Image (cartoon, each protein chain N blue to C red):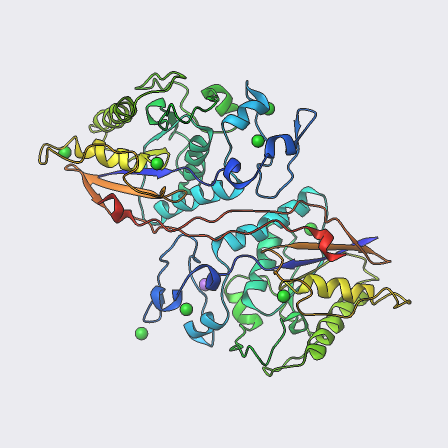
Length: 259
Length: 259
Ligand SMILES: [Cl-]
Ligand SMILES: [Cl-]
Ligand SMILES: [Cl-]
Ligand SMILES: [Cl-]
Ligand SMILES: [Cl-]
Ligand SMILES: [Cl-]
Ligand SMILES: [Cl-]
Ligand SMILES: [Cl-]
Ligand code: NA
């Protein structure tokens, strides 16, 4: 048997800070104003506005990702096939994971629009993605010749259409890598873990045990860098090969209280 | 002019987890059960009971200290004289700081009991310190030939005695390095920042009748790895050369919810 993994992105800048882009950018020059912010930010076609719509990970989000990769390495588990949602936070999580794993640099992050989160009409969000070349320029090890399974527009979709996207991409990834037999990881969003379970269960013949896809099956999102694991064939949910994680918060010190 | 810094220790294992010692130790052997726990625990005379009394930093706690050292390095600021409370969390913060700084191996951690937190009779605690030799074996760059300014016992003390301890050690450190003129850091507890300000203002002759020392001047403790800065002579409270930090929490995932 081989492993298929699903990993939620790490801690997000936009959820950790307030109006960070206007605070940190003086004109078009980014200034790091907190130790948990990125050291620098790569150019992107959408400018600093792109980063408002498409947040980076914090330093801790990179670290969270690296700890998972390190956990896999310690467990003696290799990875060959890495797919990420096109959201910057997911690509960066993939990279931090690869860094912790010490994967050979020939292992590339394949950016797969099939893995992007639900484009809910009730939550119109600005969609802005960095291109493979822009992500490589940033120093991310992205596959420049990967042709994705799913082509996605910027428009809202139904829930059915969403789950079909994810299922096509995940099942195609698993099917296409079967001859090689290397381990697979999907790096995406909180929902990705449940999508992986649904997709791989649906590869069996008998559909009687298979539950319909639901948004909102659970009330809370799985934590940052939550790791789900299956082994197969046949595909079964199992304990991942490294432990889970927990960290606490830490607020921002104001030196002026020292008077 | 010269820098003197004060740094609170990073995130503590005992405040982040519950009964982590009985949970992780199986037949006197430590097993890492969370990614944010230490990879291994160094031998100490007090064994697992010692770790109950004298918590390690979490992985994040090391990373927080590293971010501060890195931030100092980015700002072009060197450090020559490093003093740490004998609490394991403080010595580990000192090492993470030095790792981020890429300090020369000749820059050693001087374990100074003068810097230890208040021993309050209302709050009796087990006291169990790792020896400089045990710390060096753990891989901490501790100064073996350091002779501490303050010898300290296991007994509760009055608030006056506590502040006197801290001031003796901090003034001695600042007086004894003046000729050399290297930058100094005191790595300790939340109170260490206010102790440094009080000790260095008392080295001035400009303004006598400063604020009496107070436990409880503020309602909340400064954040993990909160960094305070003074420059002098004459000693002025100033902005540190690197930014503050903030991170959010992240809970522990239970893969069994996937089934
Ligand atoms: Cl913003
Ligand atoms: Cl400009
Ligand atoms: Cl590998
Ligand atoms: Cl969700
Ligand atoms: Cl405990
Ligand atoms: Cl032990
Ligand atoms: Cl305090
Ligand atoms: Cl002075
Ligand atoms: Na860049």
